[PDB]
Image 1 (tube, rainbow over the protein chains, first blue to last red):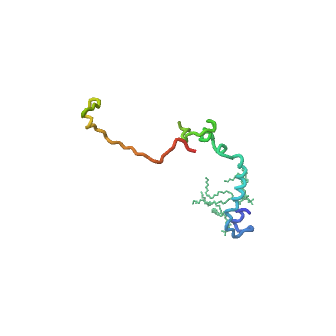
Image 2: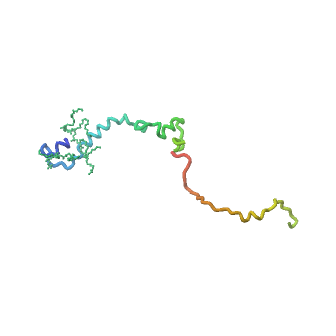
Length: 70
Length: 37
Ligand SMILES: CCCCCCCCCCCCCCCCCC(=O)OC[C@H](COP(=O)([O-])OCC(O)COP(=O)([O-])OC[C@@H](COC(=O)CCCCCCCCCCCCCCCCC)OC(=O)CCCCCCCCCCCCCCCCC)OC(=O)CCCCCCCCCCCCCCCCC
Ligand SMILES: CCCCCCCCCCCCCCCCCC(=O)OC[C@H](COP(=O)([O-])OCC[N+](C)(C)C)OC(=O)CCCCCCCCCCCCCCCCC
């Protein structure tokens, strides 16, 4: 039920003390469309600027944490 | 000395009054390693 329509107290809703939660579930479901588009670290940023990219190019080898600077 | 030879170079008594200013140096038992996971 719409949060906007319940503001005037003229359609179906006079007192709705949790009307400000009405669009949380729809907004959460719509955000689930990018569940697989943004999976893992590499899909949320430019990975070559992050530390894990360096470990992969070194053959999945551990590097000192400041390797991106030297 | 007393029937014994201990060969040493010529001692310099001026080395006693050598101005050696103490410098700060702190040891941290528990610090940083090389690599971390
Ligand atoms: C050029 C192109 C051509 C142009 C011409 C053609 C185009 C013409 C129009 C075409 C259609 C347009 C659609 C809209 C008009 C429709 C008219 C109508 O009657 O519809 C009624 C229609 C009927 O209801 P319904 O069909 O039953 O259900 C509707 C929905 O399903 C869901 O309904 P709902 O009511 O359940 O949704 C509720 C939801 C609706 O979603 C929203 O609108 C998002 C609202 C978020 C903003 C809230 C702002 C709060 C106040 C801020 C004040 C300052 C603002 C400064 C802004 C600066 C920005 C940086 O809002 C909320 O959730 C409210 C609660 C928010 C949580 C609490 C926040 C407040 C407290 C925190 C305060 C913090 C500060 C405190 C201190 C302040 C300092 C003193 O209801 C609608 O409102 C429809 C809107 C749905 C979205 C449509 C989007 C379509 C895509 C278009 C692109 C996006 C455009 C909108 C972007 C807005 C900016 C984000
Ligand atoms: C630059 C920013 C400031 C702009 C000016 C100030 C505008 C107010 C601030 C913006 C608020 C926008 C976010 C909130 C949106 C409203 C949310 C809401 O609850 O509204 C539901 C309400 C519903 O009210 P209701 O009375 O119908 O039902 C509510 C009943 N109770 C309260 C019991 C639940 O609708 C509104 O839009 C009210 C807000 C109106 C604000 C209009 C301000 C201007 C008034 C008209 C101009 C008059 C000029 C003189 C006219 C001369 C004669 C012609």
